[PDB]
Amino acid sequence: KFPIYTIPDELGPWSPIDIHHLSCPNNLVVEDEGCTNLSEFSYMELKVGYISAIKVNGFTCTGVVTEAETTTFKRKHFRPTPDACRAAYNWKMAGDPRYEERTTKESLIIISPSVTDLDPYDKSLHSRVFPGGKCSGITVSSTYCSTNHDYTIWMPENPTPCDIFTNSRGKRASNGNKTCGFVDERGLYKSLKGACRLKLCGVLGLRLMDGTWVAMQTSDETKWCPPDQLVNLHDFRSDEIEHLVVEELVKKREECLDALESIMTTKSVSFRRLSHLRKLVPGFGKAYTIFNKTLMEADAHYKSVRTWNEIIPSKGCLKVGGRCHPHVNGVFFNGIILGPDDHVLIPEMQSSLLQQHMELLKSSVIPL
Amino acid sequence: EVQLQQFGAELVKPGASVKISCKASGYTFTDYNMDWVKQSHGKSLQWIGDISPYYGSTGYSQKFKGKATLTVDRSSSTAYMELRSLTSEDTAVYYCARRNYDGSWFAYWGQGTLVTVSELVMTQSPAILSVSPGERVSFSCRASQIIGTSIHWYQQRTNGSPRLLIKYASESISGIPSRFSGSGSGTDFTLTINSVESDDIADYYCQQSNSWPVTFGAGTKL
Image (cartoon, one colour):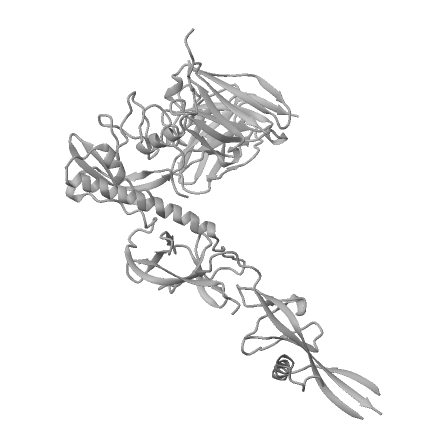
């Protein structure tokens, strides 16, 4: 995900530049070129943490007819009515003494603790009490569900559930009536490229490529996710990951600003400082080098690197574009000078190699 | 020249380890990286990882992280790989390989060590080929995405090391007969051999070098 190094797989011609035309690279937007207008906005997200089974409780309303004639009781069944059932429910809940009860009487019994599990994708409800274990949901046309007895209905004791969201603040990235993505509250850029429309707990939103769900008004037409699609929880570990990445990118951006400013005030363009101008994220950027005291740039598209051996296969080889890149004197772009013995030296790789130290050929061998 | 000496075989026990050796000579041991590949009985070649004898940097495919460990000894010019917690699924032939000067295609292979225990996918078509000698034949290798012309064709006779026949889908190799040729454009590559002969019945693998990690085709048998 987060590379150990970035080398350009595409590179243009070296043009001589003046130091005033140097700039520290943008490491925020990831491969959504042209989308650079940032507008601070708000967006919805899944609440942070684990989301247990969303329970909503209801009540089963069954209808009987009791005939008493001169201590003999006949008992018949009939299918009830929603509003009457809820009136009986208010009776039994508020403690109204009017619910306890050749004369016949119609009674409506209401067994209260009938819990159901609510699907967040579609607001369907799940309990063994429905036909097939599932009801379509409680819309406003259908204020009740059916049971397998088909003479007893189920109604919710509706008062909060689907309280699985939060309102976060971020930055919308665009370039004119097209939003490519957004910086989220953690500070990491997420791309809308390839997302699909997902309606979660009745809230219209989008599922990104990485499986995260957000809710934002997109000025574009996107197709719906298939009925099979799922979204990822907003677990604390995802926030940890984003915090680590953003921490690093901020740190290295400040270090690059200190380097660029230390170049302006001195006009001393070394190779150590030039490495701080490298683009740390896959995408289009710039590459720099120094030929015969002259300071030049080139357009480039940086590709994420996974291992150090990928770009150094042999003695003085810097694999760029499939073949080893040429060196003038002993330097390449972004300060990858050839080493003391014509090997390739990358500043980041040297730092990486050092922290692995203590490991090989302790060589505390002693003479005779 | 150049030789990559390997030892014959090791018979190991489930759950134990073994350390395979690869002594390189003919070139400077530190001037090139060292790769390692696994080949099960009647299977294709699978890249395990590589090591730089100078820096000591290692690269591993996710399948072998924790299973294989790469080391070197620069005084003796010998690379070692250790396999611990062996299961029956680890019984295979383990080759050590040496790539080109730009690390695109495999230049040299070792004898191989059969250890006995008791990404871009390359869709290679067909698995088996049954035709008579003297005919002209051509099999296909198709990549999961665009790879330009970054693919190489290897021939492997029985109990032998793979031998590179074509580099970059069309370029010939000096010392190898003129019967082999390729046609590469985009995703679909075809290796054609005219005038099939007796020593040309073997397994043929295609290998891409466009993206990391390195992957091979399933293989085509004659």
